[PDB]
Image (spheres, rainbow, N blue to C red):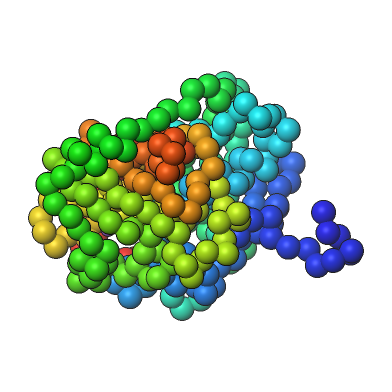
Amino acid sequence: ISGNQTGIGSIHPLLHQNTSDFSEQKFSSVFTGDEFFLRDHVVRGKPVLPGVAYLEMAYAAINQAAGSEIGQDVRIRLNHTVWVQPVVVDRHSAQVDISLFPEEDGKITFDIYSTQEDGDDPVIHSQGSAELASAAETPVADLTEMSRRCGKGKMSPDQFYEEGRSRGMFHGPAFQGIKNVNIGNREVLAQLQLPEIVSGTNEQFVLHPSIMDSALQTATICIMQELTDQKLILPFALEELEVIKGCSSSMWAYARLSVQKADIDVIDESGTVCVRIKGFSTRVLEGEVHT
Ligand SMILES: [Cl-]
Ligand code: NA
Ligand code: NA
C-alpha cells in the first residue's frame, strides 16, 4: 500500500483499481491503445483487446479477491470462458471492468464488461468461471516425441506473421512470440520466445499476453489445417485453463485437435507443463470487428 508515501499505482497492468462495494467484488482498468497488448494486436485496422488479456485479468482479480485462501498448494483454474463481444480501442479509451461472484459450491463466476457513460447498460465482453484447486501433480511433456511427430513441415515466423497480415490479423513486435513451428498431423509444436521489445515485463504477469497469445496463435495454426485457406479466426471460448507453474521467457506450445477445438500445453525448457488449456475454439471473422 502506497497511500501518501508515494504515488498509488495499478494493482496489475490489466487490473488497475479495486472498486469493490458491499454488493460486488470488482475492479476497473482504463486502456488507451498505447499498451503493448493493444498496439500490437490489431484486427483489420482496429486495436482489439486480445482474448489472453481477459484470462490474465481474471487470474489477477481472483488472486486479489481470494487473498490468503491462496496458499502455496492452491492453484487457480479457469473453467468455461467465452469471449462474447470485442473491446475495440480505436478512437477513444476503454474502461474495462471485472466483477467476481463467489458461489456456494466454491466456484467463482466472473463478468468482464464496459460502459460508455455511468449507469448505461453494460456491454458484456467475456464471461467465465473459476475455482481454487489443490496443486497436485505437475504434468510433463516429452518434447522429443512431440518434435518427432511434428515432422511434416516447418513454418517460419516470416511465413506465419505475413500470412496473418494478409488475412487482416496484425501481430506487432510484442506479439511475435513464435520462433519456429513444426507441423504434425492434427498437432503442432511451436517454439516461443518473449519478444525483446517486452523483455522487461516477464515478472509483471503470470499469464504473459505475449506468450499466451503466441500459444493461441500456435493452436490457430493447428485449427487452420482443417479450414478454408484465408479465413481470419479469433478466440471464441475455452473449456479449461490451469496454471501449474510460472511461465519463463523461452517456452514451447504444443497444440492438438480434440466446432474444431484444440488442447494446448505451454511448456518450459525443462519439459514441465506450465499452463494447460483444454477445448480452445475459434470463430471466423468476416468484415470488420464491430461492437
Ligand atoms: Cl476491424
Ligand atoms: Na486474439
Ligand atoms: Na491467427
Residue 65, placed above or below residue 203: above
53 or 99, nearer to the observer:
53
Return the x and y of residue 68 as percentages of the image width and height: 73, 33
Front-lying residue, 269 or 188: 269
Which residue reaches farthest bottom?
Answer: 91
Q: Which residue shows up at 55% across the image and 67% down it?
A: 31
Would residue 264 be seen by someone viewing this image from the given angle? yes
Q: Is residue 142 above or below residue 88?
A: above
- Can residue 167 be seen in this snapshot? no
Q: Nearer the viewer, residue 80 or 242?
A: 242
Residue closest to the far right? 5
Total numbered badges shown on the rendered structure:
0
Query: Which residue does the image show at 39% across and 42% down from the upper left?
Result: 266
Question: Is 80 placed left or right of 56 in the picture?
Answer: left
Instruction: Classify 174 as above or below 267.
Output: below
Tell me which residue sits at (33%, 52%) in the image: 191
x and y percent of residue 277 in the render?
38, 37
Q: Is residue 31 left or right of residue 240?
A: right
Q: Residue at x 69, y 55 (%)?
A: 11
Which quadrant does the N terminus fall into?
bottom right
Q: Tell me the quarter of the image containing the C terminus.
A: bottom left
Quarter of the rendering containing residue 41: bottom left
Percent position of residue 118, x then y = 62, 63
